[PDB]
């Protein structure tokens, strides 16, 4: 006994992901320290992008051996210790384009 299909028409927020995935592939995330400008690790770099694409409000990451709260809305990191930074999103792309 087989019931059969159910909803093969109603679109889904899974197949379209291809868009976000096709982009995320190339992305860069860096944080602006007090008077220094450094970037996150190759593993953390994504931990942020994933939150910016997943429509998240904020993502926590280990910075300086201490958990920090990175807010995408404003793109700024903050910790209960007394340190705050600014996160910037950059797309890795190189090619001669006018439009």
Image (cartoon, grey):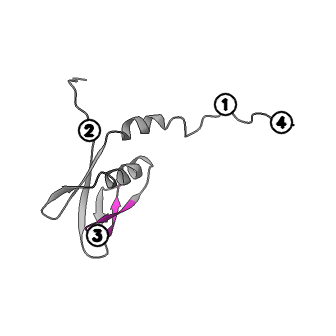
Question: Is residue 93 shown above or below 34?
Answer: above
Horizontal and vertical percent for residue 28? Answer: 27, 46
> How far apart are labels 1 and 2 at the CA level?
36 Å
Question: Is residue 32 shown above or below 92?
Answer: below
Give me the residue at 45% from left, 49% from top. Answer: 54
**Disc number lying in front (1 or 2):** 2
Residue 69 inside the magenta-drawn segment: yes
**Disc number lying in front (4 or 1):** 4
Find the magenta span and give its range: 59-72
Give me the residue at 59% from left, 38% from top. Answer: 12
Which residue matches tag 4?
2
> How far apart are labels 2 and 3 at the CA level?
27 Å
Tag 3's secondary structure?
loop
Question: Is residue 56 shown above or below 2?
Answer: below
Which residue matches tag 1?
9
Q: Check the image and name the residue furthest to the left.
A: 35
Which callout, 1 or 3, points at the residue further toward the start of the chain? 1
Q: Residues within 10 Å of mark 3 (few under 14, many from 20)?
A: few
Which callout, 3 or 4, points at the residue further toward the start of the chain? 4
Which callout, 4 or 1, points at the residue further toward the start of the chain? 4
Residue 66 lies in quadrant: bottom left
The disc at residue 65 is 3
Tag 1's secondary structure?
loop
**Disc number lying in front (2 or 4):** 4
Which callout, 1 or 2, points at the residue further toward the start of the chain? 1
């Amino acid at each position: 006994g087989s019931s059969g299909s159910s909803g093969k028409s109603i679109r889904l927020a899974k197949e379209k992901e291809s868009q976000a995935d096709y982009i995320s592939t190339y992305v860069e995330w860096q944080y602006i320290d007090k008077n220094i400008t450094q970037c996150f690790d190759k593993m953390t770099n994504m931990k942020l992008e994933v939150a910016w694409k997943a429509k998240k409000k904020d993502t926590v990451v280990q910075i300086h051996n201490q958990d920090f709260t990175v807010d995408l809305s404003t793109n700024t990191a903050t910790a209960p210790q007394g340190q705050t930074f600014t996160v910037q999103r950059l797309v890795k792309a190189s090619g001669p384009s006018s439009g």
